[PDB]
Amino acid sequence: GVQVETISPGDGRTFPKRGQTCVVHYTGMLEDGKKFDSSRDRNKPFKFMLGKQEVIRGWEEGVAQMSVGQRAKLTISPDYAYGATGHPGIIPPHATLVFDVELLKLE
Amino acid sequence: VAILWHEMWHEGLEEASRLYFGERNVKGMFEVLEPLHAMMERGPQTLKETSFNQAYGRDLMEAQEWCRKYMKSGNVKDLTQAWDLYYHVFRRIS
Ligand SMILES: CO[C@@H]1C[C@H](C[C@@H](C)[C@@H]2CC(=O)[C@H](C)/C=C(\C)[C@@H](O)[C@@H](OC)C(=O)[C@H](C)C[C@H](C)/C=C/C=C/C=C(\C)[C@@H](c3ccc(C)s3)C[C@@H]3CC[C@@H](C)[C@@](O)(O3)C(=O)C(=O)N3CCCC[C@H]3C(=O)O2)CC[C@H]1O
């Protein structure tokens, strides 16, 4: 559902636990590299909580495998992203999404 | 009915975002959001409403503007500029 390739290694021991807020910096792109969003651009980290279903499944499973400090490439199948619906005017239907996500800290 | 502006908004913005992001229903989002902004228009009559207003008064007003921009342009991007601010207020409120 979600592939996870490492760009930069993390400390390999600090994995997010449920109810924790992952502070991150991401850049989401469509299969072909087309950027549709990025926190780095806004220069404001992104925070959210795991297991609360706040974010799509690809991220829920994907980020859960990342340790603090790690930066990875997440390739999410439409099943774990926006399905046949996609997101009107932003994400098309059956879109595979690619996110460049860096797990900065846990609070 | 007695409810603090803080709770009225935390709860409202959550319902609004669910209908739009979760159900793709831009319609139910405005139905929920609308009355909230209208009340603000009426002005604060208590110390807590006033301070809540001094804190997030502007942000909310701008977000409501970005929604109006959307109503006129049909650009899903103007609608998201609003949600960037609603998120912001929502975060601080929790
Ligand atoms: C209701 O179902 C859930 C909906 C959710 C929807 C996608 C779009 C999420 C959106 C979010 O990350 C935000 C934080 C959360 C929600 C909207 C909901 O979970 C909501 O439900 C109770 C909730 O808890 C929040 C806290 C309520 C609060 C009042 C509203 C916050 C709104 C925030 C909006 C933000 C950050 C948007 C802006 C970013 C830049 C701007 C400018 S606007 C994000 C946008 C929306 C559109 C998409 C293409 C994208 O570009 O991100 C994006 O890159 C994306 O796909 N994201 C956001 C980054 C993390 C991964 C993914 C995602 O899961 O987003 C997916 C999972 C479902 O379980």
Image (cartoon, coloured by chain):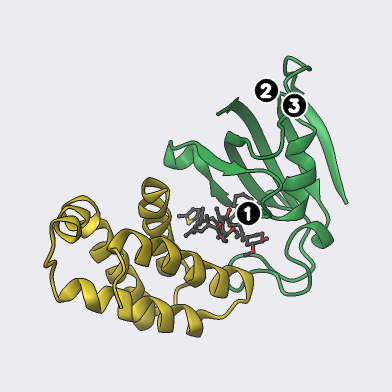
Chain colours: A green, B yellow
Classify residue A100 by image quadrant: top right
Which residue is located at x 56 percent, y 69 percent?
B18
Residue A42 in percent (x, y) is at 43, 42
What percent of the width, then of the height, locates residue A50?
A: 68, 43
Q: Which residue is mark 2?
A: A68
Assess mark 1: CB under 8 A from ligand 1?
yes
Q: Secondary structure at mark 3?
A: loop
Q: Amino acid at mark 2?
A: Val
| Mark sitting earlier along the chain (1/2) | 1
Q: CA distance from mark 1 to mark 2?
A: 20 Å
Residue A66's x, y, as percent? 75, 30
The quarter holding residue A9 reads: top right
Q: Amino acid at mark 3?
A: Phe
Placement of the N terminus of chain B among the 4 image quadrants: bottom left
The answer to whether residue A93 is left or right of residue A2 is left
Residue B31 is labelled as none
